[PDB]
């Protein structure tokens, strides 16, 4: 859970949404 | 009984890069650079640099 | 309390578990390409002058 | 509330060379409600103090003038 | 299952050097119907173990002896 939380914290948890 | 190439840290492409590159400063830099994992923390630490 | 620097060096790292880092070093570590990113909002919102 | 550990410093120096003239200025210290080990370290400190004082004297007396005007005739 | 081949190792050193020490310690090897070379190779291994032990003790007495102050009076 801690690494999952750190990942969700250091990224983001019309605008033209783009996939990758 | 001694070496499973699939279940191993250093697989065959890194052995090819070792056997094919010229010994230089830049090759040492590359072989350090290819020891980075495919972890999401590695993606984060690569995005920051 | 006393002018003995040696024990002062000893009585800080006495199997020191928690190693908290200051905000200033964590600021100057990362470069400018991610400092303005909204992930770094807590470092940004106390950089006001 | 402590210091560095004591160094190795093997042997007793005054036992092997008791003939040096620093011994009569060494032999006055004594243990008084004091064990042998702390008195031994105090003896080591007094010995290195007396040897430093003695080499300071032997430096000062030889560097008043390293030549002299009196040595011209001989 | 097996091991390396044994090296050349020609000569019977305790016979060719009887004036050497530690030959008292070497002789007490039981031969409970042991054949004529496996006893010889056990003897070889015991000989190198004994000279290794002897040179280890001569090294440890050569490093215990730093030039002392007690021999400095000579």
Image (cartoon, coloured by chain):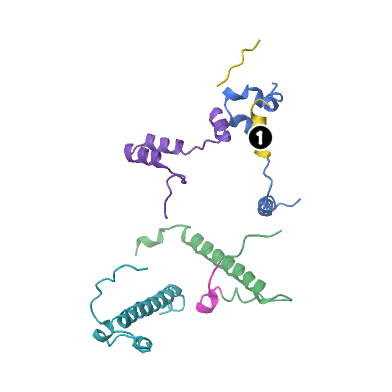
Chain colours: A yellow, B purple, C blue, D green, E cyan
Query: In front: B38, or C35?
Result: B38
Examine the rendering and report whether any part of residue D18 can be seen.
Answer: no
- Residue underneath mark 1: A6
Name the foreground residue: C37 vs A4.
Answer: A4
Q: Is residue A20 above or below residue E42?
A: above
Q: Is residue B28 above or below residue C38?
A: below
Q: Is residue D68 above or below residue B6?
A: below
Indicate the position of residue B31 as horizontal and vertical percent values.
42, 38
Q: Residue drawn 53% across and 72% down?
A: D10
- D10 in the magenta segment: yes
The quarter of the rendered structure image containing the N terminus of chain B is bottom left
Principal secondary structure, stretch drawn in magenta: loop
Against D5, residue E27 (above or below) is below
Q: Residues within 10 Å of mark 1 (few under 14, many from 20)?
A: few
Q: Chain of mark 1?
A: A
Q: How many marks?
A: 1
Determine whether the residue tagged by mark 1 lies in a helix, strand or loop.
helix
Q: Of residues C16 and E9, which is closer to you in this image? A: E9
Residue A3 is one of the magenta-drawn residues: no
**For the magenta stretch, what is the residue range?**
D8-22
Q: Position of residue D8 (x, y in %)?
A: 55, 68
Q: Is residue E52 left or right of residue D21?
A: left
Give the quarter of the image for residue D40: bottom right
Of A11 and D37, the residue lying toward us: A11
Q: Is residue B19 visible?
A: yes
Q: Position of residue E64 (x, y in %)?
A: 45, 74
Instruction: Identify which residue is drawn at 58% across, 17% down.
Output: A18
Residue found at the very far top of the displayed protein:
A14
């Amino acid at each position: 859970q801690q690494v999952n939380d750190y990942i969700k914290a250091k990224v983001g948890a019309q605008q033209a949404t783009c996939e990758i | 009984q001694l070496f499973a190439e699939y279940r191993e840290w250093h697989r065959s492409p890194m052995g090819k890069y070792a056997a094919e590159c010229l010994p230089s400063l830049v090759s040492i830099s590359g072989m350090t650079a290819m020891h980075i994992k495919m972890s999401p923390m590695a993606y984060i630490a690569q995005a920051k640099l | 309390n006393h002018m003995n620097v040696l024990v002062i060096v000893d009585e800080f790292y006495d199997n020191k578990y928690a190693a908290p880092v200051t905000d200033i070093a964590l600021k100057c570590g990362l470069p400018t390409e991610d400092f303005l990113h909204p992930s770094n909002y807590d470092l940004l919102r106390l950089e006001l002058h | 509330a402590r210091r560095l550990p004591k160094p190795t410093l093997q042997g007793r120096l005054e036992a092997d060379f008791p003939d040096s003239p620093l011994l009569p200025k060494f032999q006055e210290l004594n243990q008084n409600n004091l064990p042998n080990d702390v008195f031994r370290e105090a003896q080591r400190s007094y010995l290195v103090f007396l040897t430093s004082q003695f080499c300071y004297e032997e430096y000062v007396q030889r560097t008043f003038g390293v030549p002299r005007r009196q040595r011209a005739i001989d």
